[PDB]
Image: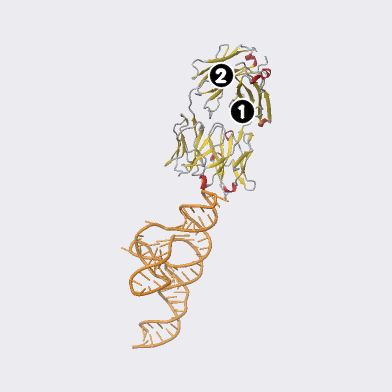
Amino acid sequence: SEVQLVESGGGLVQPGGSLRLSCAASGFYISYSSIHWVRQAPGKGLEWVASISPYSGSTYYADSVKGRFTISADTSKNTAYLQMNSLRAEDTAVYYCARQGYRRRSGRGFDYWGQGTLVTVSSASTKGPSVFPLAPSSKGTAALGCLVKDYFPEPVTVSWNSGALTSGVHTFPAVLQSSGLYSLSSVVTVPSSSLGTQTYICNVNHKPSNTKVDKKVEPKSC
Amino acid sequence: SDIQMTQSPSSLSASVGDRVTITCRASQSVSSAVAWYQQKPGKAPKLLIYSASSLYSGVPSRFSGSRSGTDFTLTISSLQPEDFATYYCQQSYSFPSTFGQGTKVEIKRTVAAPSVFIFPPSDEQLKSGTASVVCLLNNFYPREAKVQWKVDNALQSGNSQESVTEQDSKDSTYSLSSTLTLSKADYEKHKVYACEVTHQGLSSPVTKSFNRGEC
RNA sequence: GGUUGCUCGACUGUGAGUGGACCUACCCACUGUGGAAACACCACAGGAACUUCCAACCUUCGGGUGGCGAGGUAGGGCAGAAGAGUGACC
C-alpha cells in the first residue's frame, strides 16, 4: 500500500526566476494515471495548475500559467515535473502533486496528494531565526516556550526535547513582522513540579537558511 | 470560458451532531464530474466524494454527495469534532479544471476561559537591543477575545501582533499569543507591563502583569 | 430493307418519400461502451423512426433468410447499352 507522492525542488526564487518541481511516485506506476499539479497560496484556496493524461502525454494548463509552466512526465524515472519560468509574486504557493484515481474505482477524483512543496517568489534575501527562551514564572501548572524571531522564508519547525515532549504544546502561526521577516513562538505547559528537574529544550530548524538551533528553556535564574 | 464553481457558505459554525450543508454551483452543466475534498489546516486534501455522489473508499458514511442539475451539495448528517476542515468542490468535467473557493467549518463547544500568562523578554534578547513581551491565552472558546497591552497604565496601540491556533480537532478550543514589541530603550522607560484579557468565559477582565527587573 | 433473337461490346447508370438498400478492399469519418484510458491510440457495438428495396440467398412459390455510415478510392455485381458481329424469320 505504498501509494506515495513526494514533491521537491521548491524554495525561495527571485521574481522572473525558474524552478523545476519534481514529484516522485511510489507503490504505483504513473504510466497508468493522469497526474495533476495543484497549488495553494498561503491562506488561500486550491488552484489547479496543470495535468498530463496517460497513454498520450497530452498536457493541459490552467490559463494563469499558460506558457510559463510546462508539465511533463518521465516514465523511466516514475517522476513527473513542472518547469516554471518567469515566476511572479503571485506564483507563491505550496505546489501539490495529485494522482487522478482509476476510473472504475474513484472517477476523476484525485485520490492521492503529496505533502506539497512551498515556492516563495520574492527577492528579499534569506535570514535565519534568532530564538529566545520564554521561562516560567511562579504560577498547579505554568507555561514555557521559545520565541523564534525574525527569520525568512517560512518554514521553521519546532520540536521539544527532540520530539520527546509533544503534549500540551502550541506552536503559533508565524506572523509577518513589519520588517518583512517572520516571527513566531512555540509554547508548552507543564506541571510546576518538573521545573526543578526536567530540562526543557526546544529544537528549531530553519532549513532555508541551513539553520538549526536548540535552546534550553530554564526558569527564572533569580 | 471556464466553468465557474461558486461555493457557499464561505464559512460555517455548527454544533456537534448538527447537519451541515455546503453548496457549489457550476456556471455550466458539468454532468456529475464533481469531487469533494476535506482539508485539515496544513495537511494535503483528502478525497471525499467522486462523481458527485459516490462516497470514496474509507470516508465516514456521515458525508455524502448529491447533485441537482448544476448544483452540488456536500452533507454531514452529524458533525464530529474531527470534521474541522476546509471543504472544496471540484469539477473535472473539462480542462481547465476548477475548485470551489472552500468552506471553513468550525466546531462549536461550551465556553472556555483562557488560561493566561505573561512573558517578560529574555536576557539574551535585551543584549541584542530588542525587547518583546509575550502574552498567552491558552485553550479557550469562543475564539473571539480582546487583548489589551497597557504600559504603566497606558493602553498601547499598533505595536502588538497576535496570532491564533486553529480550532483544536479534539478540544475544539483556541490559543492566542499577543506580542508587544519595543526597542530596548523604549522598554527601559517603564516599570509595569500588563496584559488585559476580555473573554466571554471571563466575568471580569483578567490582567497578568509584571514589573521590570523583579526576580 | 425490315423483324426478331443470339453473341460480343465502347460507354453509362445504380436514381431517396409520389421512392435509393448489389458486393468487396483500403482510406476516411460519426455515436456509444470498454481497455489502469476526460484527449490520443486500440477493441467492440452501433448509425433515428416509419418506410422502401431484394441488386442477394432459400422456397412446397404460400413465404422465409439476411442486409443502411446517402463519405472517399478502387475493383467487381446487376442493369442498360452506342456500336459491332451473328443467325433465324418476313
Q: Position of residue B207 (x, y in %)?
A: 55, 15
Residue lying at 58% horizontally and 11% vertically, measured from the top left: B152
Pointer 1 chain: A
- Residue A115 picture quarter: top right
**CB contact under 8 Å: marks 2 and 1:** no
Q: Which mark is on residue B116?
A: 2
Q: Position of residue A63 (x, y in %)?
A: 54, 40
Q: Which mark is on residue B208?
A: none
- Residue A185 picture quarter: top right
Pointer 2 chain: B
Q: Along the horizontal axis of the image, is A72 left or right of B104?
A: right
Considering depth in this image, is C34 or B185 the residue closer to the camera?
C34
Residue lying at 61% horizontally and 28% vertically, measured from the top left: A166
Q: Position of residue C58 (x, y in %)?
A: 41, 73
Q: For marks 2 and 1, give the one nearer the viewer.
A: 1
Label 2: which secondary element: strand
Considering depth in this image, is C44 or A149 the residue closer to the camera?
C44
Decide: is C82 above or below C22. below
Image quadrant holding the C terminus of chain A, namely: top right
Q: Amino acid at mark 2?
A: Val
Q: Position of residue C5 (x, y in %)?
A: 39, 82
Decide: is A77 above or below A41. below
Q: Amino acid at mark 1?
A: Thr
Q: Along the horizontal axis of the image, is C10 left or right of A142?
A: left
Q: Which mark is on residue A166?
A: 1
